[PDB]
Length: 151
Length: 151
Ligand SMILES: [Cu+2]
Ligand SMILES: [Cu+2]
Ligand SMILES: [Cu+2]
Ligand SMILES: [Cu+2]
Image (cartoon, rainbow over all chains, first blue to last red; front, side):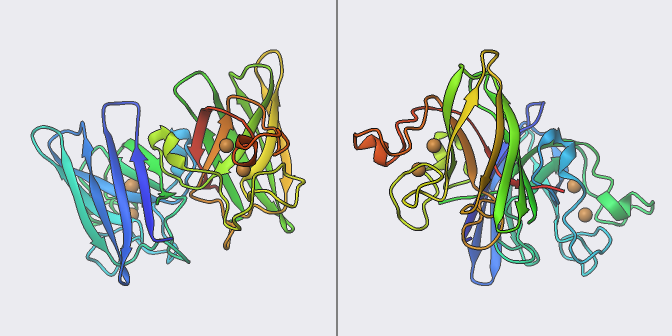
């Protein structure tokens, strides 16, 4: 309802803890992700909270308005399109995002859905091939977790 | 949501997959859990979907109506009180429960909360002692997972 949390795990070294808090009429996303390669990594909400086949069973990006993939500042984007997180030379990425389209309740609620951090940078729907318009060319899912209600 | 799933994991060998499906004004819970010691094991929905400290961070039983702990057929029970699952000699528990109090939507929604399989049998609030009234004397949490939206 007001606060949520996600613990990111995968088959590699990438781990992290993401916190979500409804503040006013928006949602603030914070936390950190370690064990990444330096550089940008796509960071999205995928539709299902199903981890029966690791991160693969989370499905595509959460997209209740049926739009094409984009960057978080675009009109045309998926609700789950949170852009990229940037890791330092030590593999650490600090997440500090304010997003208008996600919610913690109602139609846009991401509770019970999956947060994924990807292998490569998300090209924000501007790569030029069909895959850019679905995933940003963000590639494999390095770690993920189901978003749960927190105290 | 009309369907949900949860993958149970812990620090030991207990693991499992639980499916949830709304049917009528009930939730049908099916699945299997392996790696258990033969006999009954308490099986409850805990309040928070927070795995930051393993299963310990899931909090107490989901109890929105502030009742004492009971068995699933009791009027005085927590919403998250699903009774016991039973493992056979090979440590395999088959899950098949129909419950009318838990839900996949609205106020009693368990999406984003934690399913827990316990060390001991749940005494269903009839243990004679005080601990019975809170947890059923089910003991340790062997495995847990956050309940997620499924396809
Ligand atoms: Cu993605
Ligand atoms: Cu997208
Ligand atoms: Cu319990
Ligand atoms: Cu209880």
